[PDB]
Amino acid sequence: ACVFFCEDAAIIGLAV
Amino acid sequence: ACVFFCEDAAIIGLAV
Amino acid sequence: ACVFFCEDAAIIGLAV
Amino acid sequence: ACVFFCEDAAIIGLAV
Amino acid sequence: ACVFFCEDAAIIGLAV
Amino acid sequence: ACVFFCEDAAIIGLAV
Ligand SMILES: [Cl-]
Ligand SMILES: [Cl-]
Ligand code: NA
Ligand code: NA
């Protein structure tokens, strides 16, 4: 999987 | 966030 | 370039 | 893998 | 949105 | 091109 940095607010890492 | 269209098969829209 | 669908709120297309 | 919609012109789905 | 790291060279963080 | 950070385990930068 890959890590993405997106704002969910707050900016966090997300594993896809 | 961003909508990604990924296959896990089923092609799923992911809320990332 | 590629089109991404992300919320900027509102969800829109974005050309990268 | 994920489907990207990109052009280089025709827009196509790229399998990544 | 998501932060993408793309090269246009200079590698730029993009607010998408 | 964009740099993705992905693992399949070592995490590496993938050039897309
Ligand atoms: Cl994993
Ligand atoms: Cl273009
Ligand atoms: Na990961
Ligand atoms: Na485009």
Image (cartoon, coloured by chain):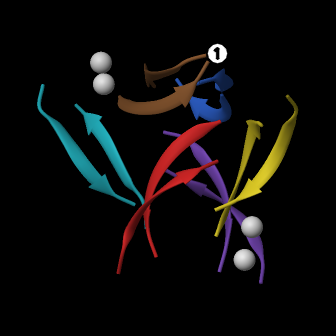
Chain colours: A brown, B blue, C yellow, D purple, E red, F cyan
Q: Chain of mark 1?
A: A
**Residue B10: x, y in percent?**
64, 23
Answer with left or right where residue D1 lies relative to residue F6.
Answer: right
Answer with left or right where residue C14 lies relative to residue A16.
Answer: right
Secondary structure found at label 1: loop
Asked if B16 appears above or below D8 in the picture, the reply is above
Answer with left or right where residue D2 lies relative to residue E13.
Answer: right
Q: Nearer the viewer, residue A14 or D12?
A: A14
Identify the residue position indicated by label 1 in the image: A9
Asked if D3 appears above or below E10 in the picture, the reply is above
Q: Residue at x 77, y 37 (%)?
A: C8
Return the residue found at the far left.
F10
Answer with left or right where residue A11 lies relative to residue F12.
Answer: right
Q: Nearer the viewer, residue B7 or D6?
A: D6
Asked if A16 appears above or below D2 in the picture, the reply is above
Q: Amino acid at mark 1?
A: Ala
**Residue C4: x, y in percent?**
70, 49
Q: Nearer the viewer, residue D7 or A6?
A: A6
